[PDB]
Image (cartoon, rainbow, N blue to C red):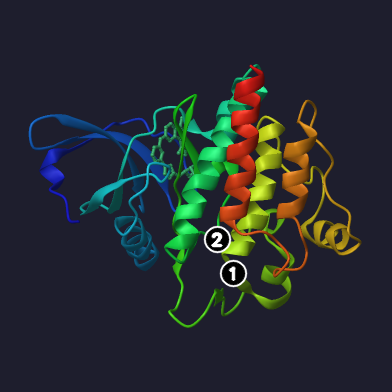
Amino acid sequence: VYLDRKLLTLEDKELGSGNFGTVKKGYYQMKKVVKTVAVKILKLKDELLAEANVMQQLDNPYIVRMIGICEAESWMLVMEMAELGPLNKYLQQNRHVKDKNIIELVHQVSMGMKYLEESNFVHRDLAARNVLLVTQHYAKISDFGLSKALRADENYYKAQTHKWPVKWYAPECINYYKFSSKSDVWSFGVLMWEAFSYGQKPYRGMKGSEVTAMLEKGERMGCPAGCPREMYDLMNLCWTYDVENRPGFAAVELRLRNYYYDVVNHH
Ligand SMILES: CNC(=O)c1nc(C)n2ccc(Nc3nccc(-n4cc(N[C@@H]5CCOC[C@@H]5N)cn4)n3)cc12
């Protein structure tokens, strides 16, 4: 859990910011090899510790691995490096990634979210900026800063006061401050839209209030160019207003698994 700073080599040039601070590339001298790492630097500490506490409990191929934490110049969250970076930035810079490949990546995210749902954890920040690419064909979920372990007696987490990405938030998050695996299903639908739109921001040119007003009328974002009808149908199903009627990640992952192999068969 607690790493030796002397074994941690940090690169001078940062990968970027992120509201919590900065993301840096480094190396952690392991048992026999060297491990390339992405480090979240604080430069709030309670939030970094809670994020690391969540990530330590997670063991899945589609969730970023936390190597550990390190208390030095600043508090550091050390993760296994996914070299290609955020899914949204990647797709914005590689607009010729095939449709089959987008299905493959969004299906990988649903597999990680299926695992997260079974573990009874709520992510609360499921966005394409929080999906990291190991390879063009390998996605992982990172950014567990707003993540919650659900109580043994409740299916939701209730926030006590609203700095919220409203464009990814389900109506019950807004109206009742209630966060569940089904609200992550809503955000996953927004994430699908972003990915099929090659990293375009959702609800372009709209205020958070205008987004809520649109969703309340029953209006939804349109089909991104080239997106198969079946994928846009799944997107819309993730955007079911009623929490109970909205599918869980086991149903969402199965629709994606089947459609992915169907597209793999056609090809
Ligand atoms: C700030 N920019 C980058 O993070 C970034 N830029 C480039 C060019 N990268 C390349 C590889 C890489 N790898 C990598 N692997 C494992 C974990 C991470 N984590 C990054 C975050 N937090 C970010 C907050 C800011 O938004 C993006 C993220 N969600 C959480 N985990 N990162 C990251 C980046």
Q: Nearer the viewer, residue 53 or 237?
A: 237
Against 227, residue 127 (above or below) is: below
Please state the horizontal and vertical placement of residue 194, each as a whole percent of the image.
Answer: 68, 39
Q: What residue would you read off at disc 2?
A: 124
Residue 256 relative to residue 193: left or right: left
Residue 52 relative to residue 261: left or right: left
Mark 1 and mark 2 lie on one chain; the one further toward the N terminus is 2
In the picture as drawn, the residue positioned furthest to the bottom comes out as: 153
Against 251, residue 97 (above or below) is: above
**Label 2: element kind:** loop
Would the CB of label 1 be found within 8 Å of ligand 1? Answer: no
Disc 1 and disc 2 in contact, CB within 8 angstroms:
yes
Q: Nearer the viewer, residue 105 or 22?
A: 105
Q: What residue would you read off at disc 1?
A: 179
Does the image show residue 163? Answer: no
- What residue is drawn where x is 65% and y is 35%? 259
**Quadrant of ligand 1 in image:** top left
Query: Identity of the amino acid at label 1?
Result: Phe
Does the image show residue 207? Answer: yes
In the picture as drawn, the residue positioned furthest to the right comes out as: 217
